[PDB]
Amino acid sequence: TTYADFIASGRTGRRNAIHD
Amino acid sequence: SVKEFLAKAKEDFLKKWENPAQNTAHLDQFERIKTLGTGSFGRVMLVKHMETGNHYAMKILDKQKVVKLKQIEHTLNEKRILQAVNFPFLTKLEFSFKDNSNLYMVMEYAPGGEMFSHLRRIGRFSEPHARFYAAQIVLTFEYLHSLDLIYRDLKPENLMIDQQGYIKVTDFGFAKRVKGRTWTLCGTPEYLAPEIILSKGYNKAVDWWALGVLIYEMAAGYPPFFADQPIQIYEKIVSGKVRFPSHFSSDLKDLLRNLLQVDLTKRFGNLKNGVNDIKNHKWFATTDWIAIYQRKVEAPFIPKFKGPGDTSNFDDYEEEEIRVSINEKCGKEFSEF
Ligand SMILES: [NH3+]C[C@@](O)(c1ccc(Cl)cc1)c1ccc(-c2cn[nH]c2)cc1
């Protein structure tokens, strides 16, 4: 499931801004 | 009238934009209580203003770290904007000041914590739950955009919940007053419009794309474009393909196809009818926009609240001193702060 893939991914925690 | 309300709001804004408040408190006036969160060059702490006993959130930026990250101009934008705006879903800047080491911005405390925390824990929000938050963002962008402000940092992590369950937008580090196109690559991978990723000049339409991402994430429990690395997220964003959960209503899906629209000539928010394309969309048919602005709508989720400076809705962060060098750092760079 898409939820299962999300939960197993490395980006379920707080996501940092990008700055370039 | 909305247009008339906005006309007057702009007069209020411009007076403060042109003559910003400066040096309106001092660190020694506050008792530091708990770190509420962190960023690359700063932190936010719950503090108590001693003379009133009011609680506030105090954003503390290390000037040296601001410089190393090339965020001087962006930080001056944040403070100048925050001190000038006034809207129910924005945190007022109550005070600001600086010392040898740091920049300080004191704003209202939102005890409900980050939307992010509740979203992840609960898994996803019902459509009415998401719609209630969504409407507050629509109104806030309508306000900011009317002031020629672009926001650029929309995400659940940066949407604070107040004691009544309403939203506060607090972080203006990427907010900019710009009438034309702008070009800075900034924001959060999951929330980037294609225009940004593709290194085009872009405008406030990127905020309306970010709204689509947020509504999707709120209702699905995960964002529309995700992967383990940012490069893979960017390829998904630019490819021009979104899949919706089967539980998404037909109206929700149609709203999202028009917000998460790569074609700027068709993206809602961006067209002739502007924000009314969004407000008058069928998914929002039950929304009483006036009642949302007046905070007369019952929040579908209202936060657990035990005392004035209670922090149970926030995560725990390592506490780190607030060090103030005996030498002034970066004086020229931050002179106007
Ligand atoms: N949600 C974002 C961050 O965690 C935060 C922390 C550090 C920096 Cl530099 C930027 C943003 C935050 C936490 C709490 C508050 C807050 C709480 N009440 N009022 C504002 C605002 C931002």
Image (cartoon, coloured by chain):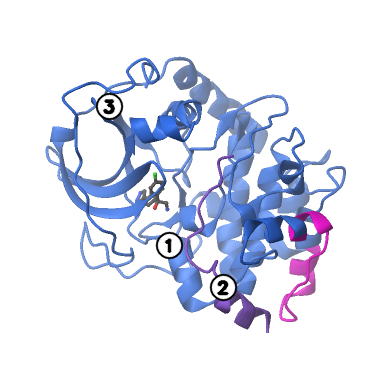
Q: Chain of mark 2?
A: B
Residue B72 screen position, x and y as percent? 45, 27
CB at disc 3 and ligand 1 closer than 8 Å: no
Q: Secondary structure at mark 2?
A: loop
- Mark 2 and mark 3 lie on one chain; the one further toward the N terminus is 3
Q: Nearer the viewer, residue B197 or B205?
A: B197
Q: Is residue B285 visible?
A: no
Q: Secondary structure at mark 1?
A: loop
Q: Amino acid at mark 1?
A: Gly
Q: Nearer the viewer, residue B99 or B307?
A: B99
Residue B61 screen position, x and y as percent? 34, 37
**Do the residues marked 2 and 3 share a common chain?**
yes
- Mark 3 and mark 1 lie on one chain; the one further toward the N terminus is 3
How far apart are the two marked residues, 3 and 1, measured between alpha carbons? 32 Å
Q: Is residue B247 magenta?
A: yes
Chain ID for purple: A
Chain ID for blue: B
Q: Is residue B73 magenta?
A: no
Q: Is residue B333 visible?
A: yes
Q: Which mark is residue B79?
A: none
Label 3, on which residue? B98
Report the side of B113 relative to B234 (left or right).
left
Q: Chain of mark 3?
A: B
Label 2, on which residue? B125
Label 1, on which residue? B165
Query: In this picture, which residue range is highlighted in magenta?
Result: B236-255
How far apart are the two marked residues, 2 and 1, measured between alpha carbons? 14 Å
